[PDB]
Image (tube, rainbow, N blue to C red):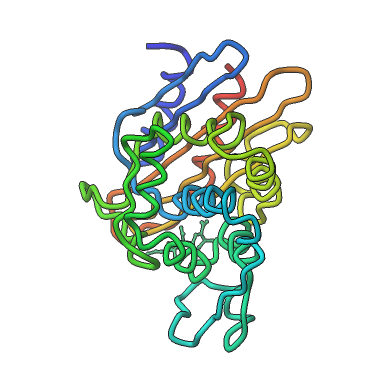
Length: 261
Ligand SMILES: C=C1CS[C@H]([C@H](NC(=O)/C(=N/OC)c2csc(N)n2)C(=O)O)N=C1C(=O)O
């Protein structure tokens, strides 16, 4: 195994948990994988697929992102800091996508899922763009239970990195849609301690975090260094104890190890 894989394996061993990494370097389209074909609970990193699926819908329904969506008291689930500010009012699908992506808003994700016809509508878009691995099975908040061995609401690092590349750097989405997703990811507020923390601060990053049961702590990112082609990096992490604490430091250190090599 490679030098970078030995360092990631050592980071994993020091952490007590299970680490999954996929890097795509688009300069030479080379890859670094660590447990790259293992399934991991996506938690909120699945919100990228849901937001992109609604963006795909907007390529035919041109005004879709401006459509108001009612926020009812019954719709509110925990960890919905934006949607809770609009109960008994409305948010547009663009505002709900930005809330889901940039504040990890769970109610906002549920509105995206409903716009897509349920969790099967999110999986549907994954399959449409060639991702045979992603599966969304539940709504918020239960999709983050992150139970060991449970295949629901999982993907592999290899699949998610390839999908994130297609959605942002590729053209799985239309031109305005692709640029909109990139802007949303670049404006994420929840990732300062995760992949971003392990990379040189001159680099531009768009990312989406996730967290859940079993101390599951995730981040998926597109990375624009100055002077070289972009990178796609997925870092998934999960732990043996159901009540384990989040470990965003592991994602930061994984990104740092990757950036070194
Ligand atoms: C900032 C947050 C927290 S709310 C969101 C969501 N996670 C949960 O609601 C969750 N469910 O637990 C069963 C959770 C959050 S913290 C913990 N120990 N568990 C998600 O991942 O979509 N995501 C992020 C994030 O890190 O991006």
